Image (tube, rainbow over all chains, first blue to last red; front, side, top):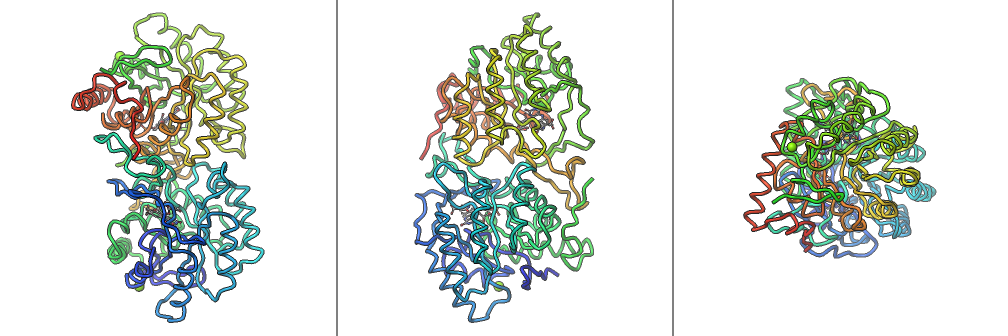
Length: 311
Length: 311
Ligand SMILES: Cc1cc2nc3c(=O)[nH]c(=O)nc-3n(C[C@H](O)[C@H](O)[C@H](O)COP(=O)(O)O)c2cc1C
Ligand SMILES: Cc1cc2nc3c(=O)[nH]c(=O)nc-3n(C[C@H](O)[C@H](O)[C@H](O)COP(=O)(O)O)c2cc1C
Ligand SMILES: O=C(O)c1cc(=O)[nH]c(=O)[nH]1
Ligand SMILES: O=C(O)c1cc(=O)[nH]c(=O)[nH]1
Ligand SMILES: [Mg+2]
Ligand SMILES: [Mg+2]
């Protein structure tokens, strides 16, 4: 019932882990491969291995989560070597996704060049929430910087490429970004990354709950579904059909998944809920979505994909 | 215990309604005057009376609310006439707040000029989430446009003035805005307005819940407290002491109020929760905050104001 076609590949279902959750090590990845997830993505990597920020840097919240991991990862070469070896085993239907988040534009270009030159036949995801010039907003909030980077990337990168974007909150911003993205042969857009720089407080202790950035961190979970759905829908109605969408943000139940698909998302990623529940979540949410579809008499995602009704 | 000093005026407590909620008519305003609210603010007005968007345009949600009211209001003259007459009765400790959200820069300047010329001795709040040039983001997301407007405003406006701002999600944005705002003799900054363009879906009906903007609307309530607290705190540590802060966003319990005050807010505004509960909320939340203070042995907000601890 959930069979999905994305980036010209076939997947058993649309579910995937969100980058950063349960995908740090080869062991994490193997557990994802073993789960019911239709596909999985690696932790955003940088050129060098990164320890990340001081703990505590992640906290479960009643309505979601807050984090400031600091891009901890085992380095580009570690992930590239892993995906290259699994690619050869052909023991998995559907390509693996490879996320990169260079500490700089030069680092992103360098990693993209290595992926291009390698035999990697999978899908690449460029995290545009990656660092940028000192007195500059995250890359994706700097429209000029974003367009400049993408133009250089597409002068040489011919393999499947998608971009992970932060949430937008103004319709003109969606228009500007859509216009920038539509000029490129992008495989997809993934909305959204966590809601940036939120703050959570322990009232009793009268203090923040994470050590880095004075307690400020990305927000995920139920807090952000309204924003995540909006971004998925806003891009669905603005992007050229060539560019598909991956919906990410506040997905925990089959109903949440149903809502993202209704908005136009083709693949779905689970972050916070997966972090709390573990790989077993995929089997649960898959069954939940199928039950919803059964009650409505739907046999394929195509029966409702992108059919969100306006009043 | 909650006595507060703000904009050089004295208030029985920091609580107020958030603009747009329970402040449309003179009758609404009188009910706010009659409640325990330490102060109140009028609905953002425009030069002409506005009917607002088609219904349904506001919906209560389990975790907050979504709206696209479309600035319905009775017109500038109606509100100005009201506050001028109440000002004379001296039957209220602390000035009334007057919100304006011109459909254009010319409209904001025109209203500010009328307030300046009038005998209004209260406080004015400029809603920088007001409309802007066609292909331009809301005013407050257009740093250049915002600075230009404020410079013109301060070439003539000498009365107390505060600005209502939308939420920001990047630290560099807070730096840029703080730098722009610190150059003016502003009375205060009010963070935050609703999280813009969120989307809520009724999965059974497979449709949005508000009629305008294809269902997209500002999000308020529990969904946004993490973002609201972050904005209050981020500005508290960047604004010159001359500019105080009004905390708005996800305030429903004494604990929520405690958190905003801990961040640096001096006055507090309640939107969503007030819309659901009615003016009686002020008596409840006041008691809730006082109980929290009593348990901690605090006798004045000064005992913890802005004392949020980092790890
Ligand atoms: C602990 C943690 C680490 C994350 N790491 C990444 C990362 O390396 N790259 C990326 O693009 N997104 C990262 N994200 C963001 C997620 O991919 C996802 O966009 C976010 O958590 C919103 O989804 P959710 O509501 O299901 O959590 C991370 C989120 C969390 C909570
Ligand atoms: C129905 C409604 C109308 C609103 N109207 C205004 C308005 O005219 N001007 C303004 O500055 N903010 C307006 N707001 C935003 C609030 O003042 C407040 O910033 C927002 O609801 C976030 O607070 P909350 O979490 O307590 O709801 C409105 C919010 C709602 C729900
Ligand atoms: O590694 C992290 O801290 C991180 C990266 C990213 O893109 N998003 C997030 O929420 N955390
Ligand atoms: O009147 C409205 O629609 C409105 C104005 C504003 O500033 N904020 C909001 O959430 N709604
Ligand atoms: Mg599997
Ligand atoms: Mg009163």
